[PDB]
Length: 79
Length: 80
Ligand SMILES: [Cu+2]
Ligand SMILES: [Cu+2]
Ligand SMILES: [Cu+2]
Ligand SMILES: [Cu+2]
Image 1 (cartoon, rainbow over the protein chains, first blue to last red):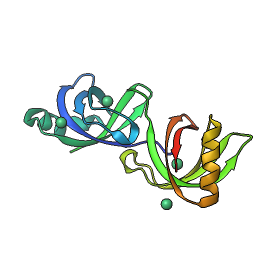
Image 2 (image 1 turned 90 degrees about the horizontal axis):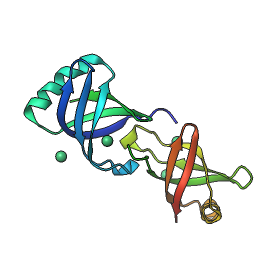
Image 3 (image 1 turned 60 degrees about the horizontal axis):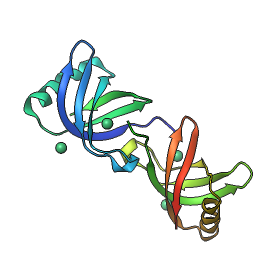
Image 4 (image 1 turned 60 degrees about the vertical axis):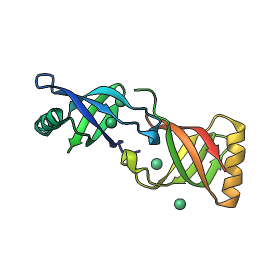
């Protein structure tokens, strides 16, 4: 019942420092019937952006958590 | 974006054939930050109520899938 905090991983493919949005090509999440795909997340703390740029440069898989409210995706944490 | 279909397992602890609900003490689902706890699922099909009553008698872990709409949890499958 408490709000879902979804663990994911993927490659960061885009970032927008204006709209405070990040594009991740995420892996499948079979626990909730979700396939691998690419989507945008608005990051819930705006200071989260910095680390993501590193990943964006490197092209490395990263772990992250996020919330899914209807059609919106809010990025909560990233490594 | 496609609708979440959440897989779980647990023990059926109650059923209500009027409100069409089943109470399952489900295991943790770490993928979505959810702990083990007890909650109710609304069912649609009578073969789901049947299987659930079996499980209710036996006390067996069962697998199940469900959708989460606001406060409702709607059962999609259940399997002894
Ligand atoms: Cu990959
Ligand atoms: Cu997605
Ligand atoms: Cu158990
Ligand atoms: Cu629950």
